[PDB]
Length: 5
Length: 5
Length: 236
Length: 236
Ligand SMILES: N=C(N)c1cc(-c2cccc(NC(=O)C3(Oc4ccc(Cl)cc4)CCOCC3)c2)cs1
Ligand SMILES: N=C(N)c1cc(-c2cccc(NC(=O)C3(Oc4ccc(Cl)cc4)CCOCC3)c2)cs1
Image (cartoon, rainbow over all chains, first blue to last red; front, side, top):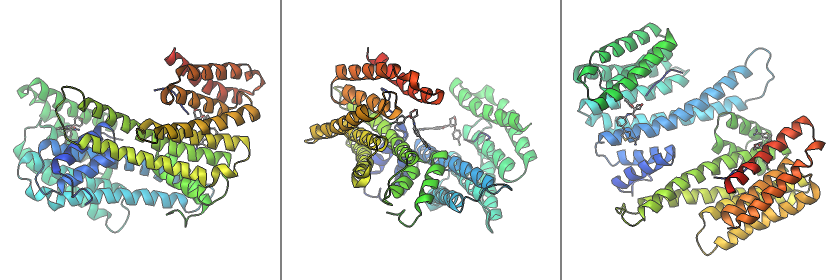
C-alpha cells in the first residue's frame, strides 16, 4: 500500500 | 520480562 | 458523551497517556471528549486527535482488507461453500469502520471546520475530511459510492486551494495533504496519471523551497518529500 | 450473552477469522460465546480460547506497566504534581484488566474445569486458572493480594500434580505449565530459587525424553525447552 500521513 | 506461554 | 464530566485539560492529559500506552481507542475517545467541549483546538491538540483516529481506523482498515481477501477467495470458482460467516464478519468490521469515520466527520462538521480560520487549522481539518471520506470510499459499493468519492475530492480540493495560497511549498501539512490526495487519485479515483503528476510537482516545488528552512524544518519537510518519492517509485 | 443467537460452529469460524485479522477482542468474545454454549471444548477450541484472551490481557498488561511506570515517576521526590489523572487512567486500565481476568476465570469455573476429565484438557484449564490469577496478582495491592497469590499457586499446583502423573515430561502443555509456574515463583511469590529449580528440572527431564519423539513432536517440545533456557539465562 502507498504511504499516507 | 520472562517468557510465558 | 461519557467524557462530559471530565475537564478538558484532563482529557488532553489522558490522551497523551493513552498514546504512551498504545491505547489508541482510549486516546480517540479522550480527544473526542476534548473536541466536544466546544473550544478550538491548538496545533498539538489537532495532531493528538488525528493520531488517535488514524491509528484506530488504520487497524480497522487492515482487518477489513484481510477479511475482504478471504471473502473474495471463498467466492472463486472451485471454493467450498463456508456459509455466511466470512461475509457477516467482514460486514461487522466494515460497519464499525464506517462508524469511526462518521464519528470523525461529525466532529469536523460540528464544529471544527466552521470555526477554523487560520490556514494551518483549516487545511489540516479539510485534509482529515478528505481522508475519512476516502476510508469510507474504500469500502463503499452502493448507490452512494460516487457521492462519497466526490465528498473526499471536494474536501481535498478546498484544502489544496487554501494550501497553495497560504502556505509555503515545504509546509508539512501542505506536503501531507498532497501525498494523501495523490493516493486518493491513484487508489480511489482511478486517476493514476493525476496521482503521479501531483506527487512529482509537489516534490519538485518543495525541493526548490528547502533553502529557506532551518535544520529542523528541513528534516520535517524532507521526511514527507521522501514519502512522495516512495510512492512515485511504487507507481513508475 | 450477545453471542447467544449465533451457532457454536459459526462462533468458532469467526474466532479463526478474527485471529487472521488480528482482532483479538473479537476473537475472545466469539470464543466466550462458544464456551457459553455449554459443550466441552476440543483441543483446537481450547487453544483458540487461550490465544484470544492471552493476546487481549497481554496488551492490557503492557499498557498497565507503562502507566504504572509513569505513575511511580510522578511520585518521586522532585516531581511536579500533575494531579489525579495518571492514577485515574492507570486505575481505568487496571479495572478493565481485572474484568477480563474475572471473565476468563468465570468461564473456567462455569463450567470448563469441572467437566474436564482428560489430562490434556484439565491441565490446560488449570494452567489458565493459575495464569489469570497471576495477572490479577500483578496488579493486586489490597486485603486480597495474598489470597489471589494463593489461588494462582493452588491452580498451578493441581495442574502440576496431574501433569506429572499423566503426561510425559516432553508434553508441551506440561512444559508450558512449568514455564509459567516458574515465572509465578520468580515474579509473584518472591521465590527465585524455586523458579530456577523448577525450570532446570523441567528442562533436564524433558531432554531425557526427547528420544521417544517424532520430528514434529521434537520441534514442539524443544521450542518450549528453549523458553525455559531463556528464562534461566535471564535469572543466573
Ligand atoms: N503524537 C503526538 N503526541 C504529537 C504529534 C504532534 C505533531 C505536530 C505537528 C506535526 C506532526 N507530524 C506528524 O505526526 C508526521 O508528519 C505529518 C505531516 C503532515 C500531516 Cl497533515 C500530519 C503529520 C507524521 C508522519 O511522519 C512525520 C511526522 C506531529 C504534536 S504532539
Ligand atoms: N492459534 C490457533 N488458531 C491454534 C493454535 C493451536 C495449538 C494447539 C496445540 C498447541 C498450540 N501451541 C502454541 O500455541 C504454542 O505452545 C504452547 C505450549 C503450551 C501451552 Cl499450555 C500453550 C501453547 C505457543 C507458544 O509457542 C509455541 C506454540 C497451539 C490449534 S489452533
